[PDB]
Image (cartoon, each protein chain N blue to C red):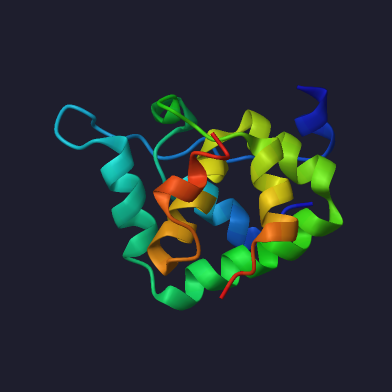
Length: 91
Length: 40
């Protein structure tokens, strides 16, 4: 993964979830949504600039690392920026 | 480079292997976020 070793070599793998009692998706929502609204908005605006300045980089990272892909989606969901039905056009 | 906020966030959720359900298209999402989205 030369792309990552060059640009994104410190990508987090994620937490370990015990999916015999808790589903990843539910954790995903409670994870982002337990955070004060300022966070999601701060991340997404900051990120928005970053991804506008680096569309190739940003998109290719979302291509390979799905936690960010859905992390962005769920934050869009929790604030009401976008709905699930607005994400399926992306899907 | 990625800002630290992003890094922490990527780590706080399930491992990327627990995400292989429906997923979203990175390329569409980025073009969507850049042009079509305005974060409140």
